[PDB]
Image (cartoon, rainbow over all chains, first blue to last red; front, top):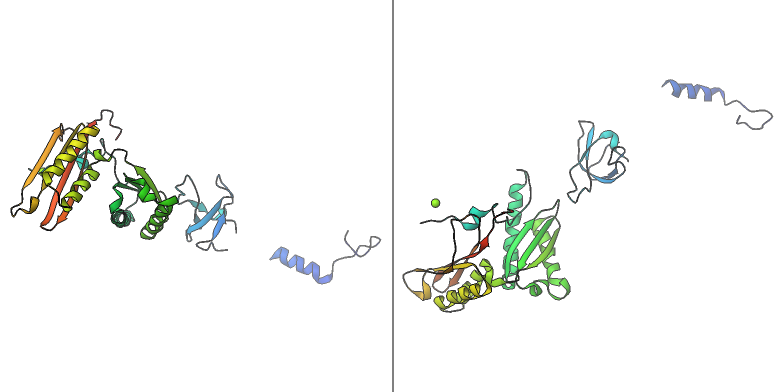
Length: 81
Length: 211
Ligand SMILES: [Mg+2]
């Protein structure tokens, strides 16, 4: 246990238990921001936000592929901020 | 009568496009307008550099301009300075970053544009039209043109009534699509108006095509 002394470990508190139980019971990709991807073959690459796929809960981030750095669209889960 | 532009009819068969890029309808016109402005500026700035062909490509968000010239040293300048300034202003015109490459045309006398420019410059600099055009054919045939034709037209020597005259050596088959006929044109602004010069140079046929 974690307490003042090893002979007698101590409880937490009266209200601490209540707070822990209270919790136990109870972000926008700005255009122009430089991002990294979270998954896929393009995961963890230096991309830069190019447009806003906002109401789709999606994304589109420019990346540097075959010199034709292509307009590349990603899921919203693919951000790294 | 009226004849089709040789390069126009042969484009895609034995001739390449001067501009080679893809663009959707949203930016095709913008690309064409930028191309026109860039070509105009470069042609005027390099009027005395014997520039033969300006190939504009648009890789991604950049523009690569290749200048085919017969005088690379003038265009380049000491240690690339002139190329640098041309690039720095082409980037301004295009908006996107720019890169410039220089391609030498080894034998300018077989280049239609350069031949037309020479004849036009001579006419403006007061020379006999017959002498000038005959001298360019002789030089073209000497350097090995399979065929050549020059046509001067309009108030030759200050004559009141404009006339058209043309020389032609070798063979210049303009109805043969597989033929390689480099054709270009020039206008000489002289004290008595505009004198048009058309030059066809036939430099062999292409069977495999290769577009
Ligand atoms: Mg017709």
